[PDB]
Image (cartoon, rainbow, N blue to C red):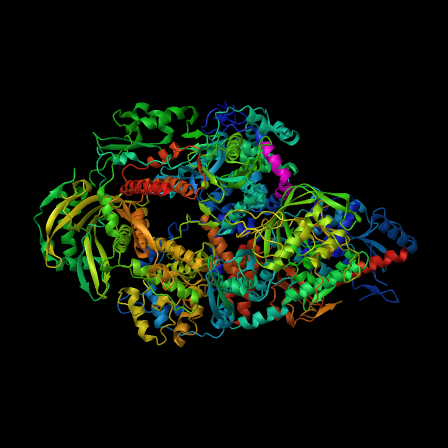
Amino acid sequence: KGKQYISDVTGCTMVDPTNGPLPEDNEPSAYAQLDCVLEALDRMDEEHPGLFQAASQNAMETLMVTTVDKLTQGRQTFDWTVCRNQPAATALNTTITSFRLNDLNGADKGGLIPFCQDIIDSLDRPEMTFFSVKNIKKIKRIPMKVKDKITKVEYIKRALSLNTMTKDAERGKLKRRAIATAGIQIRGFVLVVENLAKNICENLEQSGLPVGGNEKKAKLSNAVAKMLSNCPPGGISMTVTGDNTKWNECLNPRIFLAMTERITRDSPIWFRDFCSIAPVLFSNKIARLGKGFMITSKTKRLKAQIPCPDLFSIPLERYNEETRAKLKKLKPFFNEEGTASLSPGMMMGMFNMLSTVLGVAALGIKNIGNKEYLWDGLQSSDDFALFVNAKDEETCMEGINDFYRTCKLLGINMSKKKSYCNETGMFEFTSMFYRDGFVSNFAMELPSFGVAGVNESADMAIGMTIIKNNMINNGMGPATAQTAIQLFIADYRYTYKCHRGDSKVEGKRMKIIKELWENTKGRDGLLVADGGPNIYNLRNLHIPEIVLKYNLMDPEYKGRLLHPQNPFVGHLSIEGIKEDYDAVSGTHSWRTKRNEEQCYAKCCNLFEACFNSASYRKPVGQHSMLEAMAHRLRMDARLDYESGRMSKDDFEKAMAHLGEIGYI
Amino acid sequence: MDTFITRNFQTTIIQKAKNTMAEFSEDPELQPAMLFNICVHLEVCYVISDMNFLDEEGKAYTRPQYEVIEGMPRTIAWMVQRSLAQEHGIETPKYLADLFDYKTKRFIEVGITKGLADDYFWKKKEKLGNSMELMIFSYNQDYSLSNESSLDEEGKGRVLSRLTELQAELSLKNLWQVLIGEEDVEKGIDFKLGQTISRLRDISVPAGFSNFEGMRSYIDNIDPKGAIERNLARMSPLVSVTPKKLTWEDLRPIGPHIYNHELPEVPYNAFLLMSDELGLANMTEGKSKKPKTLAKECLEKYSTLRDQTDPILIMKSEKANENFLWKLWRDCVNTISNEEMSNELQKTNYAKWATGDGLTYQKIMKEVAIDDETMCQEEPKIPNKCRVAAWVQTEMNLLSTLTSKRALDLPEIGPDVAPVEHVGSERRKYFVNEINYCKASTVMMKYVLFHTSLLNESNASMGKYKVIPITNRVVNEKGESFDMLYGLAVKGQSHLRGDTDVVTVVTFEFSSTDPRVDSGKWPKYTVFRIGSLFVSGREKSVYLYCRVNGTNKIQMKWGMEARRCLLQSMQQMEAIVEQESSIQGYDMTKACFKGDRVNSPKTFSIGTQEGKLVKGSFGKALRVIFTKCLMHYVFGNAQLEGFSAESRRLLLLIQALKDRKGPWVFDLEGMYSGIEECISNNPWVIQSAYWFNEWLGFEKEGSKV
Amino acid sequence: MTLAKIELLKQLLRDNEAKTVLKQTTVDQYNIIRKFNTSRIEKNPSLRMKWAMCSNFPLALTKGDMANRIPLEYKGIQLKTNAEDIGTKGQMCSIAAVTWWNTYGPIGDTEGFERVYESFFLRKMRLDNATWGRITFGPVERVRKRVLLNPLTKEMPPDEASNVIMEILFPKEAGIPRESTWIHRELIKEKREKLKGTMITPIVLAYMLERELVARRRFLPVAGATSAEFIEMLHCLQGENWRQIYHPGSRSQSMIVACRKIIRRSIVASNPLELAVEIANKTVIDTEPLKSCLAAIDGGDVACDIIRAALGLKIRQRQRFGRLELKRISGRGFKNDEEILIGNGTIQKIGIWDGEEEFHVRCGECRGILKKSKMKLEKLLINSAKKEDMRDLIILCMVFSQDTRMFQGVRGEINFLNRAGQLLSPMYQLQRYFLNRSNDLFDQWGYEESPKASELHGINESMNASDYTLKGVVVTRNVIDDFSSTETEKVSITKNLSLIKRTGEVIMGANDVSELESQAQLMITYDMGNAVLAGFLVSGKYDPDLGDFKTIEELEKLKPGEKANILLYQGKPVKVVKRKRYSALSNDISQGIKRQRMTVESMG
Ligand SMILES: [Mg+2]
């Protein structure tokens, strides 16, 4: 019911529900009025002096320091060069490489601002050259890099495009939904906007600093107690347990652009423009559609997948009724290249902090028309709980109705089927059930207590630390923790074929474990990986078993296990020692075999090998790595020659090689 | 940056730099880089002007040789410069100087830069001239001095080392690159918007705005006052929560269609038999052996059943080929009993069609599909709407009872010294005492082991057909360990690298229940009569239930994690005990389970008979909870998740009704429809709906009284 | 080994991509280059490990004399192999080989192992020597606080710890020792002594020392002892419905007393700010100036916060008022001057707050929420910790609220001073007057009907668990956790030592320091160690006239004043001069400031 037009930049069909007709029914509505959103944000600013300015300044200062490598953190990202989903590091380095071919060298400048500037610039280049994977049949399918080109419009579509899939392992829902991932072009801007939103929402008491562990219980208890105290004498306080489903489909990126503009009211124009790019790229987003439909004939026992670019090449009469109607309604927004323009709404997980800020702004109205009720609540990532204090149940229901209608004006829809109300003192929030001052969070599935699959020592340390952390945070009781220890030890013994030497189990490693069982006098000092007895209990979950058994180890067993020069340890395998678990180095500290990639890999491996410090702490310098490598190699060769560790011919060869490099 | 300045510069330098910035009306906070540069300049100047004095003869040695002029107000510095020039009879520089050298009686300008020292030296000389001497130092260990005797080695080296240390510290903090030299310090972080992004911004504004500049101005200038109130007044009154006070009468039975006797009875669809299971037992010393050898030995003990080669079909489901399934079973037996050690089936071609693998459609290129008018899209298959079945209640009754055999064994943990671990040990002892011997534990262990074997063999082999025994290790009260063989399975073409495609599994499982007793429970099973047994001197027929099923690697993995049911079944109980332990000081585990001097044992309402509710011990409720978790695992799918999630709301509403919290519902039929859309064919969901209706009736009666 | 290094460097240089990346990329940017990896980490780690452990040779063995000690096979089991490899050109091995090595193999030497891993052994010593008590199964009152997870040998900011570890483990790459090495010279030397004679990989030692030196703090619920010794064992001591008694087997107090003494000395004299900063930056605690540990901890005591504000440092924005810790929640309050008559009959002109406001209030072990309007207290909700804390919190909140009832409740006089003999503002005088006479405003405050509710219960004027509570005072049998969103916003300092926000609002007060004396546990003083590369000063560029560079031991042979060629940090060839004396930039800068100011004064 909004405004339908055609995007001149991309040619897609755009829909604008913002500032549209007010809803006339109880169906979901995206027609959020801008003036109402600005009213809510102005109220939020009034109740929190200088929170917007502080958050904007903090976000700007953190952005000035953030580097390009920060984009390597996250999950699978859309890669335009291959139009696929690839890890963040893969997509980032592919984009950096393909930008060099286009004379966009902002990545080499370090900081995130120049890289994002080059990302913005890339949208203007008349063409776009990159390296694409091409498979040749030589019969073997060999993939290689080919210098491919795409004109401007296709590149813009790829940059604005959002890859899609079906969310997996989403318990509590009968039917599935669509989860989406974005490319590298919007990653940095989204990062900055999310940092700004988090800075805002950590101060808000309704949302609170995003709480983890048992801070949720404290938040719920504080909210209930505060509301009950605020309740007038002889009045009634009612809690609404609310739940919005598909509430991100009625949230408009234009509204979020307005919120970003309002939040940064007093900031340099450069940061105001920088923070306005994620909403801009989300309002013009393109939704890549799955992998197509499959049509089969059973009189011929044939099947064939129809790629999405060819959805409408088949008469609609050859689809099932539901798919027929879906395609018939999708035709207006279908793009010839196999995508559908999706301007309104927002996919899950993109703007969580910003949406929470909007929800808290809705909560902070607290009243309508100076009526005899006050409402306040908690908001977090699509889940909200409301509390209304009034003088009777009728007035509380009037307040709840007013809150519902007000939320309709901001694009926030609450599920009437999933939301209910009762007297204050019993409710639920973020799958956490409060009742009479007792909170019963029982929706966090305890992670399967099995080996983390990194190596024996590290796996044992990780498992014990995980059990202890569960005890500390998730209210795990003593007996449950002990049973968790037992289950983890069972899984650990099963995975690594390390059963007690006195057991009757057989295997390749178990024969040697049995031998060690009797060849070793001190039997309680053996690590469990060596057939030793487990000695972990609640009290000693924070001390490595290598230390825990040091005094009981036999004189030779500790030496063998703790032999300073043993072959099962390599320096390059220590990168993951930190990420956090506390352990020790020993024969059980081995690594797994490996199942511009190799260029960077080998260059950095050599860099670390020459200087063992680069692995631990960032090196410092204002010169090429090659010259520093050459100089340190010269010093090493001279030291070896002086100390007799190297011969005259070896040093002569080293100097000849260095001159070949050109540093003599 | 301010942290860097504070850490690396004294408060005096910061104060002097701030004063200098204030004199020029430059805000240090808005231009931190300029403040840092001024601080560095002051530091280097003061360092240079140290340890240098003039003796009586006037020669430099270590009255000061150097007098600092930088760092004081503009007026005071100008007075100092003019007074020095007049006293020493030297021309007063037109530009304020930094230091003054009495030995040479000259004005010295100190500067710093990031680039080559020579370039900055030339620039400064051009800007100021030769009227004053020029010392320039650069961060790259290079410098330019007009006179080399002005500064000895020590001073220049010290300033160079300080600059290098500052550079390294800045590089560590990722601030050196952000840092900008004095030439560019009078700037910001430039970020210009292009053309395409500018246009996209222009075409992404709400209705009523022509460009983004108009939107920016509107948000910056106009103040909204009563916009929410203005819009609520003109909103239609049909937009409302429509609240309605909830009452016991409003609550009604869920899924009334489950009482419709026209619908078919719910069939048994669990992966393996649970209450009807039969396990051939072979007593062993405890030595662990390969599953193939265990199955071979168990079959060898029961040679009459193994050698049975004439099937007596009892009922073929709808389409299963009796010949295919029987020949596949015989192939399984022969493979298990062969002298080889590989478990792969020896046919590999008959098994291709017996399992139905060969009856798979052939992919064709999309073009032929487009041109072929007879290739359509298969209509979605909707789950059948079934009614309550009497076998789910029987399974619930049977699985939550103590047996003579326990299959649950867990590792040991270190001794207990603290009292807390002692109470944890006591709680664990009671829990495992009331859970070790229940049949649900044996069924759970069997499921876990079978799924582990399935996943291992799927990883090992993909394109061949393998035999996987359904095996368990079961220890009884006397401490005897039996190997229990519950049947065999043929795992077929697992051409599945992902975790969302079907892998065929044909399961042949021993059982003693007559399929004709409850014909409506086994419409998916082709069952033969393979023999008879004397369990305790009494004859019992031995049937073989055959069924073709499918799995996914994710299903096998999550089956491997059925053991967490145990955890789920203890946390709960622990909480209960904790509550009691909170009510009265001493630990209530002993009191809760079997009672004590001053507390009778805890009891829970477990079921009913003839419409009268029945109570049971804490252990019985424990077994019921464990069986509930096990059934949630066994019958878990989208339907069960949806039903549980949607019925949680009704449970909480009923709890609010019980406590007299005056609950309200904005719409009740929507919630009821959401709950009832998940009750189609899952046995556990339908039985849970029946149980929920029964409990709701009991709760209504309790509310009446 | 360097032979292989140069060979592989040449091999890399063979292709042009290596040549362009190596020369184009600097040393600093290498970090980014490190993160552009495959990112092909396993999706199912546990399952992949289970599958790998069944493979014949899943371990990547090293090449060396020790590795070859492992038999080719042992009693049928093929421990290792001689097969060639393409993925890494290495050798593979079986876990059975690890078991054999731990069973039959060369016994190594273990003498420095305990010293290297002394932290974990100290943890086990604390556990072993501890004594246990009894369990209280009743509900426990836990409080959310920031706590240190494990004990530390010494607490430094991350940068200081990183520098210290760099100094210890890597004698090379130690250019221009910062103002942190001579601070921890004893620590550096003891670490070097303990870590000499050990062949353990340097990166493992670096991470271990980082754990042992960098403070790890987290917001945890604690009940009772908050020292890291108890926090490490928190998983066993604490519980939602149980409690246990546990007895495990410094510079902070000295810093507190020093800061309080500095504040007391400065306040008495005019222009306290200048005197305070002079004493602060001229102070030392046995090895270091005050700006060595003040940055180590975020915030702290009120005196420490004031001193940090006087210096250049960041502090928490939490408000302090006597013994009350206040965190604002919402609302804008305007401080306007107003003339109010006190119950004594006198009239005082004081600043009153206009506008509703709310605070998370803490005092001792008591926490609560106070909502107050202008010249009135609206509501106060508190937990139940202890009688004294309840009384103090109630009195201080009533004083802060500036309710007219408190003003009417004044019966004595307000003319008190401090230990220095100074007249205080009416607010603090009223606070002291009410604290001294607790049963003064409570009697005339008024009573209210008990908070009829399931859990909200009232507290009488006697602090006993009885009905008929004070007007607006409610006690909730719940947990109130507060003090979130620590921004450390910018704070200005006035000449009177009273901290203020970005605007004119005042957060900290000079008198907020408690007038308590503790002497000092350390030696307060008012005015071979150090580190490697400490007697040399960078001067000039490479200057290839010296040819190759020289090592530290070679460097020490040179007499003072000789030029040497050194590699600074990750390369950076520079020329240095052996220092003939010991340098101190702070002393030189102070002398320069003194010369400048004495010049100006003499001219004046
Ligand atoms: Mg909810």
> What are the residue bounds of the magenta stretch?
A37-57
Looking at the rendered structure, the number of numbered marks drawn on it comes to 0
Residue A112 on image: x %, y % = 57, 44
| A335 in the magenta segment | no
Q: Can residue A463 be seen here?
A: yes
Residue B355 on image: x %, y % = 19, 43
| A40 in the magenta segment | yes
Asked if residue B438 lies left or right of residue C541, the reply is: left
Asked if residue B610 lies left or right of residue A36, the reply is: left
Q: Can residue C58 be seen here?
A: no
Q: Which residue extends farthest left?
A: B310
Asked if residue C489 lies left or right of residue C67, the reply is: right
Using the image, determine if residue B237 lies above or below residue C377.
Answer: above
- The quadrant the C terminus of chain C occupies is bottom right
Residue C570 on image: x %, y % = 58, 58
B174, B682: nearer the viewer: B682
Residue C576 on image: x %, y % = 67, 63
Q: Which residue extends farthest front?
A: B705
A480, A545: nearer the viewer: A480
C367, B544: nearer the viewer: C367
Q: Main secondary structure of the magenta part?
A: helix
Using the image, determine if residue C197 lies above or below residue B637.
Answer: below
Tell me the quadrant of ligand 1: top left
Q: Residue C183 sits in which quadrant?
A: bottom right
Q: Residue A592 sits in which quadrant?
A: bottom left
